[PDB]
Length: 240
Ligand SMILES: [Cl-]
Ligand code: NA
Ligand SMILES: [Xe]
Image (cartoon, rainbow, N blue to C red; front, side, top):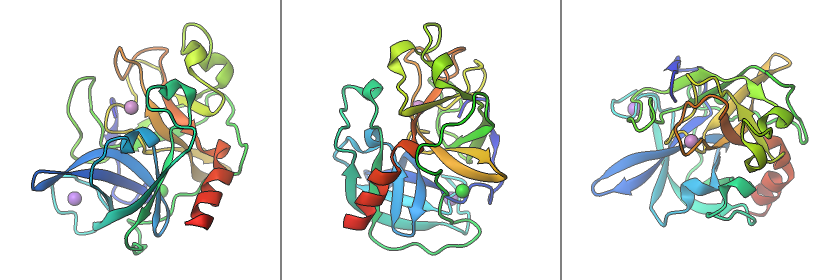
């Protein structure tokens, strides 16, 4: 997250860190949203590589003991069947991870609330991106979870020529684009939390930013629109 602020420890209890085994250690690679005690929602592109993955819930600082973490292996990966790794712009950037164990809920570990199917936010709706991604274009991961206020940019504006043009689809949510704050590498897969009817819900799964940089004016961060995939999500969890 570029231009973020440190999140309070118990603000976003559904945020997880998706990590891969690297030598004798574990490296953060993407975010995710806990949606069941044994299921996480993340981006399909995060699990393209044939790596060994684990999920950390109740995580605040990647590099220090928070005293609240639970570490759990990934038992099964279900990517959306229409996902194509060489075409992120086609959409379908979503995957569900079944955990080896069911995590315990508390003030640091909760399920993320998903929007009702078909919900589209009005232009400029209040949302926060959260994650441990790069704090600057070509920078380094954050140590502590960051948040940045990124208002939505509706489909009509987002798909206009000076924004993303044809690259953005109606199955995506755009947010931000002010040139100061944005998602960045390492934030992929995580949530876009939007306040609707007094409750935050996870409306987006972080998918991509411009190849020119993270915080680029008129290139808002692009997310998979969660409300387009409610039936798919329910179908996977029910058959697995
Ligand atoms: Cl949450
Ligand atoms: Na930690
Ligand atoms: Xe990203």
